[PDB]
Image 1 (cartoon, protein in one colour):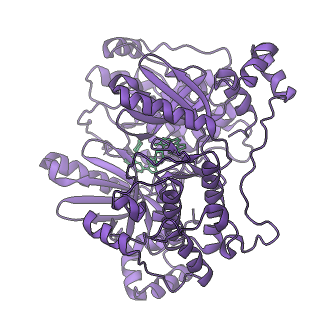
Image 2 (cartoon, rainbow over the protein chains, first blue to last red):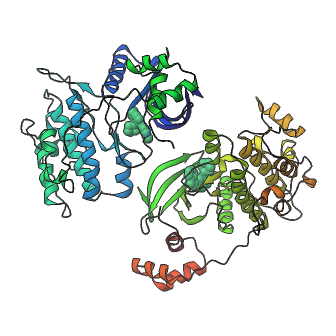
Length: 319
Length: 319
Ligand SMILES: O=C1COc2ccc(-c3cnc4ccccn34)nc2N1C1CCNCC1
Ligand SMILES: O=C1COc2ccc(-c3cnc4ccccn34)nc2N1C1CCNCC1
């Protein structure tokens, strides 16, 4: 079972109309995760949502966001070749091991906040931030995943409205209000921080009505083991009024976020320019069969084709 | 979800009338694999074979056979708490990485042969030996799994008949012939050796009729990279006449099995007496709440209950 330069292996997840398989790249031997989308069963509205997701993945390039390597498209199927995160979901990690100590939660949350603030720099809101969409690579680095519900947000625009996971949804979402975008992601990050440090959700209910009532009241329990600094940080995320909710760039200066990083304060990610001139990698690809000129054309136009994927995968360590 | 002293985690497999879930032992924190069988779906004949499998697992104690730690039984469900092998099936390993070099195949095959010869010492035939039932632990040690089709073999009797995986089945099984027991495992181990060294099955076909004819002819292709010693060893397993097939105790002396193993010739496993007197582990269990006397009674009578499982799990490394 091959597709392009990829040997398909075991299934990682199954949705309706899509599945995710682990795969090996034939030319480099690197492992990847491939989202396989059956286009035949999609209406034109779902199809445009699909191409929107691809456009967002091409915009985002951050070490803690799942990276897109290659797009293969047939009449029936779309293949999105992406990073593989071998240690799975933060959600499953919390279920198995319980709460993280604050030192470990801080390491993950600095990466999470950096990635999401970087999305907002790029005028993208994720809109479904939850523990299940935080992946972990082999070194336990965060990789934010599933931008299938994400969208651009615009000055003077309000978002078409949608509800991700209700436990992570801001109170304005329960009230059907229009919203700009980023403030809703900020609230979800407050819920995420609470789950990292406690192993549980701050707002829960036996049904949606009860959950909604608790979110709108905005009260949550502080466990005895939680530090005052962590409690104070949570107050900057879980503000009912979106106008007064902290922004991520402000929250990056928080004392808890930077404990043990006092000379390395968290700051907005600065995207480096992509090095497309590594002749060591180009020489390897010329040995494979691609011409020097083909490689420079694919890389300079950033085609997300078989050549740029090979070049990027050669820049990643083996497994 | 919990069952007894175990927190159930992700599903590892789902078959007909059973599933396998990874789990954590609450008292010790050790990971395990739990086979979960809905007894309500079984007829009395299936129920009989289920308790047969349990009896067989209690007989076998070998470092390269999946170990049974505990049995939990409710009116509706049977839980078999077993060793977890974190690196999965040899079958998937061959699919992903291709053939093993003969030195890597030799290390696995010595363990496989030791485990199966030990089964035959205990008058147990596995009857479904195949790449899918060879698991790999965190250190790539073999763990033979799934004794659901295994049986005792006896002097004077012939086996009830059953079909394992056709590609691994001995020729006499295709001809409906009665058989003693261990000779069919020996044939399957020849097929396994071939698949380890070549990455492919020796006998295949587009359908069962074609596969059957090739197995009965007993001819298979020797790749140019295979050593003469490996070719000669295969001839001792893949003998059409079960009467003339080598026994595993004889095959253990083969040059290929022992190449580079000076002062370490492969020989029948000698099962040591289980140390049930480790006062360091017992003291931990007394701290947990069990009484010293209860622990001695469960271990001395080897009950495979919550006490013996805890004692065994405390003797395993954290992972
Ligand atoms: O829905 C998608 C679509 O975008 C993805 C891109 C890459 C991966 C992925 C990479 N490495 C692994 C390892 C295990 C599971 C998924 N992946 N997954 C998704 N998913 C998962 C599915 C489950 N919840 C989290 C998101
Ligand atoms: O059929 C059974 C029943 O006996 C078992 C006992 C232990 C485990 C097991 C232990 N560790 C792992 C890791 C991954 C998958 C299974 N396991 N499995 C089975 N199975 C597998 C399922 C797939 N085919 C090979 C046998």
